[PDB]
Amino acid sequence: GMHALYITHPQVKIDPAVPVPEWGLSERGAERAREASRLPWAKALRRIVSSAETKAIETAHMLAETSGAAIEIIEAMHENDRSATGFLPPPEFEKAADWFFAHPEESFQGWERAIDAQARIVEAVKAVLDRHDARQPIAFVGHGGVGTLLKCHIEGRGISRSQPAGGGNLFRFSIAEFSAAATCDWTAMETWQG
Amino acid sequence: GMHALYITHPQVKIDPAVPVPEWGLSERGAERAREASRLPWAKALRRIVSSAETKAIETAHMLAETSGAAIEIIEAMHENDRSATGFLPPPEFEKAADWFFAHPEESFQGWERAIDAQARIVEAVKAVLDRHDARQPIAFVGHGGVGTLLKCHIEGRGISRSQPAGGGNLFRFSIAEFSAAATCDWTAMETWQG
């Protein structure tokens, strides 16, 4: 277990009454996670480290259905904080997201700065990996925004935007190297042959 | 002036500091509105009735640049109210929007009910048209969500989803008929030859 995976949650089930942060995976999202869980790479996992959001925890549990991998919840793995903005329609959100990545040292509308979200996710992954038993294959389960920031850090490139639509995407990275520049393209978890 | 137009605002300019409700049109959005303003149908307008949102008012002003049409602001023309939800990422927003239209007699997460938003926009357009001088060509400038609900009412069809991407779309309707079932497909305002 000297390479780690970072996996984004797949599709989310909306509800008119259940609090938004508590939403779980859709029928399709859950299906995809279950499909991934039966793959050799998923069966080999011994620890899955999830953000504390319901959709992430559900993904982790689904991925662990065959393996029975231990699940650890890390609050610090939360998505880029963007609660300050209130509601934003998609066209405006997309430009705001572009802005977030384009101006990492600045806050969009009270949103977490991209530089700060990157520092946070890198620190959280580092803390976990620092105390990691190298023998146990490990995956992180979380979110595309911070996942992208992590990916930038790992590759030694500047912060820039662009996972594919639908979530449930992963990349693999070297644990040893995470501790100078080094990862695969985002790929659908349920089709990953690694 | 016995047919009226309903026109959606085009693309919006984001800003990291200016309050979100106060955002105006982007360079591109403003360009498109100005282009439309120089068209014969726009030159012929004598009254433009806008919602109170900055993006709508800017659209109205841009559309009136050649005509000098009178602009009336109507608070009741506001977009479907969806402030209660807080921030929603696009994939979840799209399903929530689908839900909004699919279940018009129910509230999504404290959002305005589609049946209520439809009643509101129909009542607002009716009030304006009731006191309208039939000689003066008129356009309403506003939002795609309530615009869709208005369009459903006019056509005598049930509430259902689906304007094209980028906004700045219009349809034309008979004022006389607005007062049983009767409209063109949504079409880009700057290309409209009507």
Image (tube, coloured by chain):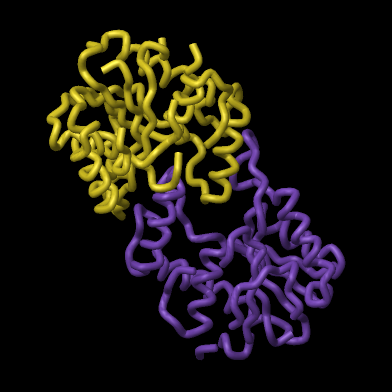
Chain colours: A purple, B yellow
Q: In the image, residue B92 lies at what x, y percent?
A: 57, 47
- Image coordinates of residue B27 in percent, x first then y, are 24, 53
Q: Does any portion of residue B136 appear in the rendered image?
A: yes
Q: Give the residue at x 49% y 11%.
A: B180
Give the percent coordinates (x, y) of residue B146: 44, 29
Q: Locate residue A29 relative to residue B46 in the image: left or right.
A: right
The total of numbered circles placed on residues is 0
Q: Residue at x 40, y 67 (%)?
A: A101
Q: Is residue B128 placed above or below B101 in the rendered structure?
A: above
Query: Is B185 or B118 nearer to us in this picture?
Result: B185
User: Does A145 appear above or below A55?
Assistant: below
Query: Foreground: A59 or A68?
Result: A59
Residue A59 position by quadrant: bottom right
Looking at the rendering, in which quadrant would you find the N terminus of chain A? bottom right
Question: In the rendering, at what x and y percent does residue A98 appear?
Answer: 40, 62
The C terminus of chain A: image quadrant:
bottom right
For this orientation, the residue located farthest to the right is A66
The residue lying at 73 percent from left, 62 percent from top is A60
In this rendering, position of residue B163 left or right of residue A143: left
| Residue A123, placed above or below residue A77 | below
Identify which residue, A56 or A130, lies in the foreground: A56
Whether residue B80 is visible to the viewer of this picture, yes or no, is no
Residue extending furthest toward the front: B193
Q: Which residue sits at x=77%, y=64%?
A: A63
Looking at the picture, does residue B7 appear above or below residue A117?
above
